[PDB]
Each structure stands twice: as structure tokens, then as C-alpha cells.
Length: 233
Image (tube, rainbow, N blue to C red; front, top):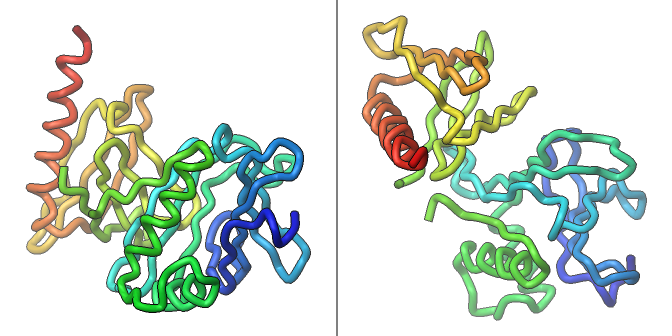
């Protein structure tokens, strides 16, 4: 852990999960085997560390923050933490503008750059060069919608191969191929409810879904159940 082997560092990223804190993200290669590593720091003391990303990273994706065009989620599922401290998805919020200014001040992007996505394809490039991959599904036309689970609101990210529920513990991650059924209920003037039944039989009820979001949801489930019908062969 030194400045030389450090790829890029981001100060002021807002970590929501596992713990909620404004920390500094660091992406670098270990001096032992040159394997990639992610670290969340508070000053110089490390709050979190995911080692051997190329191996331990199960999933990684950029997910838009609803109604906040200048903020973007980084979402990551992993196997083992630093001494197995946490075991839940790392979710954080990068400020687009700030991330741009930092990368340019670091010389990672030319001072001429003004588009934030360039910052993304750079990160995604760094993942690829080390062993793992970070997706960017929002650029099946991936979509997301607000809805309630119980009494608390949350986002629903319908991605090409996964469905996420947005970021209030517990966070939900469905393999698209794990959906066995979907039932619609509580139809109202403006909304409806949808309960997903998985293969193992778990039922999850999502509420207050805008009726507009139905078509995208059903079709999404049909196309998945469809492809699946052929994967049995």
C-alpha cells in the first residue's frame, strides 16, 4: 500500500453499504503478487478492504441514482472481506463532477474532457486490465423504478441478467433465471403490487409500483422465462 502502485484514488465518495460514511476510495495492486485491491479509508486508517478483486468480486456495476443526474452508484458483491468483517454488497455514491475534477487533477483524463462517462470507461478499463469486470447496463433496455418494500421506499433495477432492490438493508439481488413466477395484485387508480416467487420458493412483495412500469416489468419477466424455456434443452 503505497503511492507508486496506486492506480487511482477518489476522495469524498459516499459509502452507503455496508457502513454509511464519506470515505476515500483507493484502487491498487498489492506488492506481493500484484493482484488488484479496493480499499475504503478514513484518513490513513482503513475501514474496508476487498482483496484479489479478480477472484473475490462476484458482481460490479454502475447504477444511476434516481432523480440525481450528478450522482452515480457503484455496486459490488464480493466473497470475503477484510477478515470477514462485512459480507454485504458494497454500495457507494460517486459525485460525477467531483470525480471528473479529481481524475483531471491526477492526469488520468485530459484537461479537455467534460463528459463523466469517460471517467467510467476508464474505471471499467482498469477492472478489465486487472482481472474482473464492471458493467454499465444503462448505456434489454435496462430500467429502474421506485416502489415500496413494506413501509420503506426503494429502487428496482431491472438489469439484463439481474434484478436489484435499492440499497436499504437488506439489499436484494436476484439472478434473472431464479424468477419462477410473478403475481400482480392490489391494483389501484395509480399503482399495483408485484410479488416475485423464486426457484427456492421465497416470495418478495413489492408495492406501490406505478402502473406505467407494468409493461416493462411483465415483458421483462416473459422474455426471461422464455429464454429459460430453451436453456432446459
